Image 1: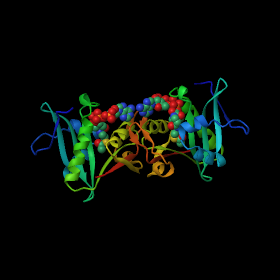
Image 2: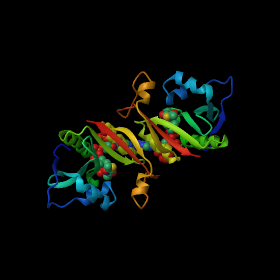
Image 3: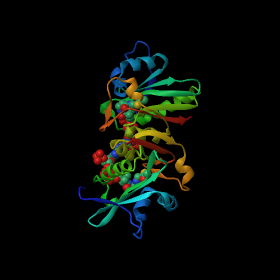
Image 4: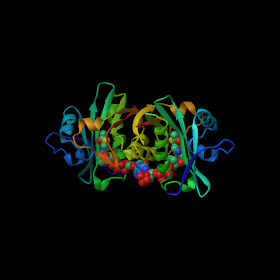
Length: 153
Length: 153
Ligand SMILES: CC(=O)SCCNC(=O)CCNC(=O)[C@H](O)C(C)(C)COP(=O)(O)OP(=O)(O)OC[C@H]1O[C@@H](n2cnc3c(N)ncnc32)[C@H](O)[C@@H]1OP(=O)(O)O
Ligand SMILES: CC(=O)SCCNC(=O)CCNC(=O)[C@H](O)C(C)(C)COP(=O)(O)OP(=O)(O)OC[C@H]1O[C@@H](n2cnc3c(N)ncnc32)[C@H](O)[C@@H]1OP(=O)(O)O
């Protein structure tokens, strides 16, 4: 909606694993990019309803390692508001490219990221097969490969 | 449906440009891969309602350069029947890989081809921008790049 607020996560505050796990089934992988990344929390009427994690590769590129919206609040435009906020945060830290990777089966998400300016740029063959023990499925398609999209900032 | 027939196009028969143009807006590009490709026609109660073109790259790979279903008959499973038939024809000619390329904005099609066994393998940046004069748009996304998918036969 139009009355959502976004702030960085504060030390001592609970980490919204419920939300992060909607986007990444591995709590181990989440905690790893929380080490060097920056977590942001989207609040609406005092409740944390969404989040994203920015994860620098280097000076030029930073990656959205995780972006999630509470299941009760999806498909109301909150994700788009989050993506706009990520774009500003990455620009403010002088990154030149913003990257996000999603599953080959995530065809709905491939629309959304392109709507906000991401171009499809790379395929990571068997990324999910190699990095997650149990296979992952969407829409009856096995999610084996990562599709990487890139936005020039 | 279950009562569709598929046959190669016969010399002297009209070429269904109405159908081919649904899949490729350039009659010039269509006629070019009709030169070295093979056109197949799907008939239902005597009417041509779909078609595809197979276009060899070399001994190992052949490409679906064009696949189309009449607008009145779409989303009834005819395209899937066509894709199954292409797979058999390519195997029968001893190809090892079957390739199809669609637009970055064609997220519905990215589902369908993966459902029938195609993996996303390659991005052709600015393919449509370079090869078609007028820009092409889908779902409010500009169609600039070709997504190439590959099936091991
Ligand atoms: C790096 C990573 O984290 S990849 C994993 C991403 N996270 C997840 O998958 C976790 C689970 N899902 C979610 O948390 C969320 O659904 C998100 C983060 C993916 C998206 O957030 P949302 O608030 O649901 O998205 P939002 O409402 O802004 O837009 C979704 C869009 O999909 C569109 N859409 C609807 N049906 C379809 C469809 N069949 N195909 C494509 N797009 C569709 C909607 O219309 C909407 O677009 P629009 O606003 O232009 O009309
Ligand atoms: C190389 C080239 O030619 S690329 C260009 C391809 N051709 C074209 O775009 C021409 C215009 N379109 C067409 O001719 C046809 O629609 C084709 C050839 C793309 C597909 O043929 P169709 O008969 O419509 O497909 P079919 O009915 O078998 O299946 C379409 C699928 O999309 C699914 N679908 C529906 N909504 C969506 C959505 N939002 N996102 C993804 N998939 C969706 C349908 O459920 C169906 O899948 P299912 O059978 O597994 O449930």
